[PDB]
Length: 131
Ligand code: MOO
Image (cartoon, rainbow, N blue to C red; front, side, top):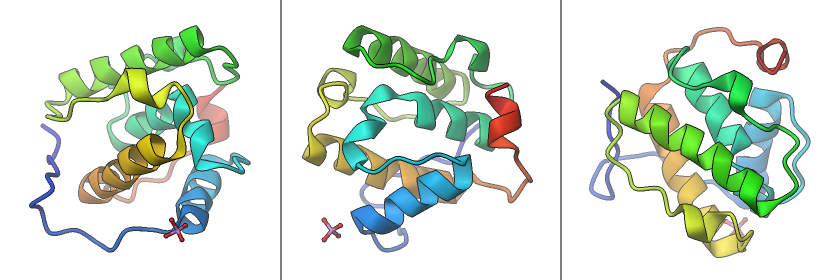
């Protein structure tokens, strides 16, 4: 299963919002300008695909979601991926989809530590993967 990451785990330094966005944008070939835009759940779904290909129902992800009920659908896809891979993290979905900075920044700081603990260096085509 996945390597879990806890508050007590030894991890890299937290990233600035600028450096976190750079990671997201460069890794996934996106152009987010705000951490709040992670409220859509789609980037997290793709990072899960990148970590564990086949863990996520990529075809069901709404990459161009603009409505909160769509953000929730994307996070349920992510939650199913976490369950499949034995990730013991509860996603505060109700908070994230509202677009508030602190909630979204807190979760992406954890998720980047999770990612770094699990990523194997595989090549990945995030554009080809969004079809
Ligand atoms: O000054 Mo920050 O580390 O982007 O919240």
